[PDB]
Amino acid sequence: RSVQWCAVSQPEATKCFQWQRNMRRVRGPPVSCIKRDSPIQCIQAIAENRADAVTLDGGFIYEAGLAPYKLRPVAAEVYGTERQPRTHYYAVAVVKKGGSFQLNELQGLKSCHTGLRRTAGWNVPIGTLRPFLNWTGPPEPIEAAVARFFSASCVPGADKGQFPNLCRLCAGTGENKCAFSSQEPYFSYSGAFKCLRDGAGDVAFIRESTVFEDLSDEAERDEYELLCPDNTRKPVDKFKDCHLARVPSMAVVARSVNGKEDAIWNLLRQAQEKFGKDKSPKFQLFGSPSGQKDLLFKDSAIGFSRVPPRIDSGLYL
Ligand SMILES: [Fe+3]
């Protein structure tokens, strides 16, 4: 049949339907869409045969690989350039130029995170800051120690009921405040970076490219610097010498048994040829419209790379 793609929002479904009409027009391999609400709803649906595929961040790749889902990664997103390509990215800590604090001096400060359980926005910074955390738990949750450490944060998807200070800086309206979706304006890489630019937080945990994709002016880019792990501040273009971790790309996952891996692969490979970076004026696979960013796949991606057979979700990570 078709490859069924899981979409986690309404604009993502809209792009999926456009991908399906574009593949038909061009007579490529068929794709069809499914609309879920979070990434776990798409992980549940693929597992229960209602969808076949979805692209995930490293922290959810972990989660989808567990029992009883047992999903595995099939294609990794390629970043960088055509000349210098890579299947990895970098977790950074961005701050405003002018400050004096370091990575070791973050106590009581205000933070912006891409979302809860995301790689560069959460797992990496909480894994790094662990010595200052003073986590006595469990049974105390990790979010409770983080809430005590930072004065206020914006961590989309965190429980505002139990941990009110982690959603305190979040900019969404009403029930969408602290939401793990595009309705919370500080969600993801650009939202976390915008929380830093707005002045609500003193540090944003993101990836290396967000500042270059969001600030096109180079002079505007000189108002920010990175917080390195040697406790030094360095400019934004020195990410390879100033990062918290080198993390593998976001990946498309499928089922480990009867997952349609080769069908998924041929779809992606064909979609990258016809609708890739500068391939078509009609449809852009690595592109989002207007008030949207990273719909289905990351906007700055330039391709896919087939993840080898018998590679685990834990062994890919
Ligand atoms: Fe990520």
Image (cartoon, rainbow, N blue to C red):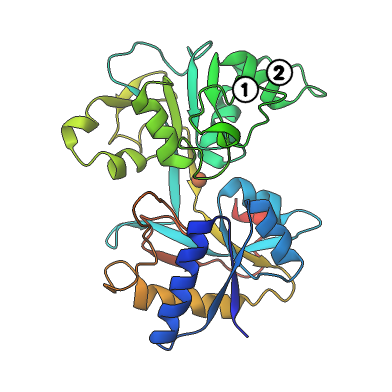
Quadrant of residue 241 within the rendered picture: top left
Task: Point out residue 175 in the picture as x, y percentages from the top left corner.
Answer: 60, 35
- Residue 170 is left or right of residue 289, and the answer is right
Cβ of disc 2 within 8 Å of ligand 1? no
How many marks do you count on the picture?
Answer: 2
Any mark on residue 41, and which?
none
* Disc 1: CA contacts within 10 A as few (<14), some (14-19) or many (>=20): few
| Residue 238 position within the rendered picture, expressed as x and y whole percent measured from the top left | 30, 34
Asked whether disc 1 touches disc 2, contact meaning CB atoms under 8 Å apart, the reply is yes
Residue at image point 48% right, 58% down: 11
Question: Type of residue at label 2?
Answer: Trp
Q: CA distance from mark 1 to mark 2?
A: 8 Å
Residue at figure coordinates x 38%, y 62% from the top left: 286
**Position of the N terminus by quadrant:** bottom right
Taking 33 as reference, is 35 above or below it? above
Q: Which mark is residue 130?
A: 1
The secondary structure type at the circle numbered 2 is loop
Point 60% across, 55% down: residue: 316
- Seen in the picture, residue 41 relative to 222 is either above or below; the reply is below
Q: In the rendered structure, find residue 135 and report the number of the disc placed on it.
A: 2
Image position, residue 168 (x, y; %)? 56, 22
Label 2, residues with CA under 10 Å away: few <14, some 14-19, many ≥20: some
| Side of 38 relative to 140 (left or right) | left
Q: Nearer the viewer, residue 101 or 311?
A: 101
- Is 195 placed above or below 118 here? above
- Left or right placement of residue 269 versus residue 252 in this view: left
